[PDB]
Length: 164
Image (cartoon, rainbow, N blue to C red; front, side, top):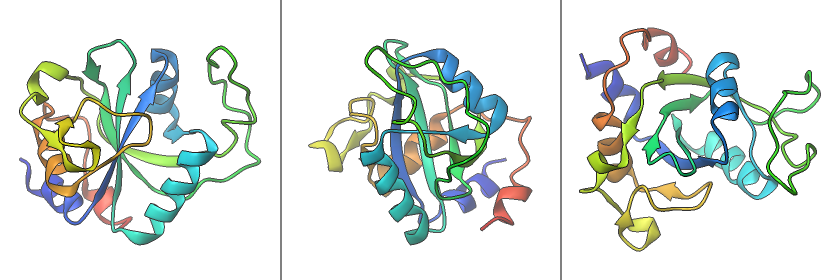
């Protein structure tokens, strides 16, 4: 069903994550972690303290799709084993230093063609697929976007609801 999912999304905040490559999203799906640039790292840390759920919605650049969405389970932390991110050109490892823990809610893809009816008030009412890494998505648009993804029956939201 979708009832527990709607409960997790209740009063949530939503952020678009744009990854330059697929390998980093695959690693995030395997290990339950994400790292972003310092500007976005500060925003996500503030949001984590402010909201019952902070949802990251992932899209690999040039893929034409979202690859899934996840909930922050922690603020960023330093000093773990260096995650083997594939770094963009001109991208350094210290820039991706802070590591957030995340719980995946959906690991299934959603093509941009399916979200063409959703616009984001916080990005000039452009289609929600449009945005820079870290762009916040207003509550109603983000909720509807998450509800468009195919159900991920491999995930049990019972743990998740408890983290809240």
